[PDB]
Length: 110
Length: 112
Length: 110
Length: 112
Image (tube, rainbow over all chains, first blue to last red; front, side, top):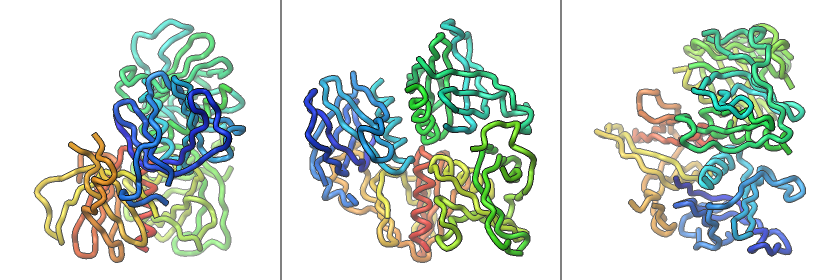
């Protein structure tokens, strides 16, 4: 199983340590071999501008859930918590797009 | 709340697994923390509405567990597994992954 | 091929004769045997309230297209024109739902 | 405008049909009435972005025709057919019907 595309995301915790504020950005995002990789902060169109990996999240032992209204005002926000205690929010306004990532990441956890 | 046609089968009765799957498509309603699967929508062609007005399966979502099913649980794609607090279990499916993800979101909110 | 569910719709022309105003309503809707049937004007939840057929549209010879911004202010509006000159608008705010109907009706025309 | 990964194959070159399908998944960009399919996204695993920066197929949408493909045109599901004014033809696909419908909407607007 693999997935690739541009998604909106922000880290929210670094191994259990909460970030002070949100840093929403669009980035190239890749799910491959049970690892989700978010590329660096940036619509984002040309592959020559997609930059390089910033964050990697192993899906083994992770949890994925819909974020509560208190966590974000954005539409279709998912919260991904890795086993090491890092946390990320992922979202896209398009149901079509957020759905494909929800499926891939949820199924990938397994 | 939400309503739509979904594929579903019961897979366990109060913790006791069923021998085989019994899939049907039915109207489905999520309202007030309760998920209701109506009688099969098919005549064998579509039934008229009055013919599927009786609930077949009602699942109270308080204490329920929702997940994406393991891929080997069914030959079908886009399967959710729902287990109620009494141990009954259901699979929920649609060929549209977007339909299923949006239902997952709604059911997850109903559980919470 | 068949499809069934609740959709928002309004007739806009009766065999080439424009309606004075829009009459948007949710209704039970069924696609079966190359015919799309909209039930009577009404969310709509209990099958005991779905009423009876109101409009039938044969898909043979029909056209389905995305409605221009001038035709409706709603989200995801499709325009269905039957060969006899009747016209309908169909929409749903959920991409997941409008997409399933778009596919079914477009493929049904063929 | 829109961008995403899609499956596509060319099926005719300037009106002349190709013998077989040549499907790949690639980054795809719709911008200003032009649909660009980049080089294949796969290495054999995913290529890094710099490796698929070159366009493979560019389709100018002025005078193009878009449709849902006949079901027998391909063994795949959710296939669109796009024919450019020079007679070249492409199929576009994704397992998600919602992805494909939203792309149909965008391409249709680009044509108009």
